[PDB]
Length: 293
Ligand SMILES: CCCCCCCC/C=C\CCCCCCCC(=O)O[C@H](COC(=O)CCCCCCCCCCCCCCC)COP(=O)(O)OC[C@@H](O)CO
Ligand SMILES: CS(=O)(=O)c1cncc(N2C(=O)N(Cc3c(F)cc(F)cc3F)c3ncccc3S2(=O)=O)c1
Ligand SMILES: CCCCCCCCS[C@@H]1O[C@H](CO)[C@@H](O)[C@H](O)[C@H]1O
Ligand SMILES: CCCCCCCCS[C@@H]1O[C@H](CO)[C@@H](O)[C@H](O)[C@H]1O
Ligand SMILES: CCCCCCCCS[C@@H]1O[C@H](CO)[C@@H](O)[C@H](O)[C@H]1O
Ligand SMILES: CCCCCCCCS[C@@H]1O[C@H](CO)[C@@H](O)[C@H](O)[C@H]1O
Figure (cartoon, helix red, strand yellow):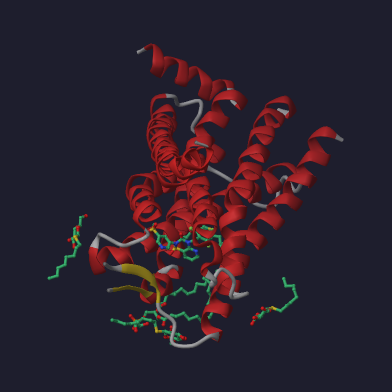
């Protein structure tokens, strides 16, 4: 009686429960991120008081988040289910490339917000910041991101069921590449950002009341980004630099860890508009307007 209910759980009840939760979490994030991030862009298009430097950059974060949610999220959901590539050789280069480009645009956008706030508050009359110069920064963020993520597209290969993965001729190249990737897309920008906002914090809490309502929001966006991107960033360093997760002792535990980590990246795109709702009264107003209409 008891042994049967253990194999019923193992062989049927747990796998379906797992697959249900996995698809439900991905679909919920997909819809919430698409609706939320479109309402961010519309809010600065409809409202003209909201067209500040920070908000022009926050719209660029949403464009990057939509790129990842529309194209990369479904490819990720199907790979996390089947553990195989079903989109052919071309999209095995394009989709991982667009994921990388999306991450680069996101972390560079947040960096330039911190840099703008750091000079706006801590060093006030050194550099001038306007919406016109913000659009030129935004285009430069895309140009850099599209270029620096070409080696990523270059190593992606689809090999025969098919599997999409990075192809490396030697053991040292993936170690150097993934070390640079982690430092450049995660550790150095967020460490510098942390130090910038700590100084902004000391200035505003050591025009002001408005700057405090927006700095507060900004620090939460950077903290949630750091948290959402930490599991996958660490897991890829452990795998590519420290040669971990090669033993099939618990093939499924490794899949579960990487699966949840992949979902968390996409969960961040759903999180940002929810943050602007509870920490920005101006955004909340145009969010209440969208649900009322
Ligand atoms: C502030 C600092 C951060 C920002 C720095 C800003 C600097 C911006 C500068 C220049 C922009 C222009 C770069 C444009 C990218 C250059 C284009 C490029 O990457 O060429 C590729 C080379 O592929 C390859 O083997 C690439 C394999 C990867 C080799 C890894 C070596 C480690 C070097 C460490 C790299 C850093 C990584 C950090 C990235 C975030 C593809 O070629 P190709 O189709 O002919 O071959 C295909 C062949 O591989 C298939 O057999
Ligand atoms: C869209 S996908 O599901 O088709 C797909 C298939 N295979 C691979 C990927 N990549 C991906 O998931 N990671 C894992 C990863 C992130 F996202 C984000 C990070 F901040 C750190 C990471 F460690 C990559 N990591 C390093 C370099 C390139 C990639 S990547 O090529 O962008 C995507
Ligand atoms: C003779 C060998 C043919 C093997 C077929 C490979 C199966 C991959 S189907 C894949 O589906 C995508 C849907 O997004 C399309 O965009 C792609 O073009 C297509 O490749
Ligand atoms: C890799 C680290 C990021 C590099 C940081 C450099 C800052 C770019 S400033 C930005 O550059 C645009 C280029 O198009 C100009 O048009 C804009 O006027 C200007 O504001
Ligand atoms: C079917 C097409 C097969 C192409 C395979 C693409 C793999 C990228 S080769 C890449 O070349 C670099 C030279 O710069 C070395 O540093 C790296 O060690 C090596 O990984
Ligand atoms: C964050 C690092 C602090 C821990 C100290 C160890 C530094 C060595 S790096 C790493 O050690 C691996 C061991 O498995 C090797 O296989 C890799 O070739 C090498 O790149």
